[PDB]
Amino acid sequence: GSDLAKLMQIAALKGNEEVLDVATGGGHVANAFAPFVKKVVAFDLTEDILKVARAFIEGNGHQQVEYVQGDAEQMPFTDERFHIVTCRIAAHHFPNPASFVSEAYRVLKKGGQLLLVDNSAPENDAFDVFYNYVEKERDYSHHRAWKKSDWLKMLEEAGFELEELHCFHKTFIFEDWCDRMNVTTEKKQELSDFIKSKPTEYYQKFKIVVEDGRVYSFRGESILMKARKPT
């Protein structure tokens, strides 16, 4: 799975790093990196978010984390400050993720790395559009899960050199997945009904399981990219 352990392994940490965790959210990435690096900046849009991240991170005894508010994107850091920028399961909320990518490039040291983890859309446009429509019905704040090719273009355009791209698939349990976003029973019925009526190709693509007329599970893709800012 695209888990934290896999991220940590791919990171190939040296122990001296200053890390920026973009859209830290519940703080899990900063939490994981903290013991193995010099310093972490946990960065997100509001104080409420940073309070929650801090409760979790300080709960595990990590004390070299600095909490900083702002926008991914338009980041209030100096050029060439970080060895690592991380961003996990967050970029699909960004309204202008190309700006986050260029800002990540800017605030990285030369030879530094971006580690980016997110859900991804198929190259096939119909499946792309469908996957994303479904994501947004379930989470109104979803902007876009981009194609792997979209990310390759954004990274190159910003000057990053991709080193590694790892792809993963996960089976989502529809009811649980919905309930994490507090979707109404009515909205869950509507979304299941919408998915269930799609033709066979869609069920085959997303390994859709229907039990007793309701969507039970489907399978999505995610990625982990390690991209270098050149020396």
Image: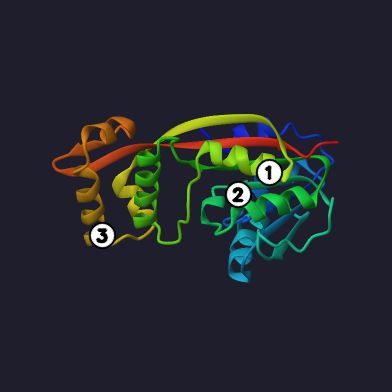
Tell me if mark 3 has few (under 14), some (14-19) or many (20+) residues whose alpha carbon lies within 10 angstroms of its own. Answer: few
Q: Residue 136 or 17: which is nearer the viewer?
A: 136
Q: Secondary structure at mark 2?
A: helix
Establish if 88 lies above or below 170: below
Q: Which residue is mark 1?
A: 157
* Left-right relation of 33 to 196: right
* Left-right relation of 55 to 77: left
Label for residue 187?
3
Which residue is at a point 58% across and 41% down the rendered structure image? 151
Asked if disc 3 and disc 1 are in contact, CB closer than 8 Å, the reply is no
Amino acid at pointer 3: Lys
Seen from this angle, which residue lies furthest bottom?
47
Sequence-earlier tag: 3 or 2: 2
Sequence-earlier tag: 3 or 1: 1
Q: Position of residue 129 (x, y in %)?
A: 38, 46
Q: Which residue is mark 2?
A: 28
Establish if 229 lies above or below 67: above
Amino acid at pointer 2: His
Label for residue 182?
none
Q: Nearer the viewer, mark 3 or mark 1?
A: 1
Q: Secondary structure at mark 3?
A: helix
* Left-right relation of 168 to 175: right
Q: Position of residue 105 (x, y in %)?
A: 75, 48
Establish if 21 lies above or below 17: below
Q: CA distance from mark 3 to mark 1?
A: 39 Å
Amino acid at pointer 1: Glu
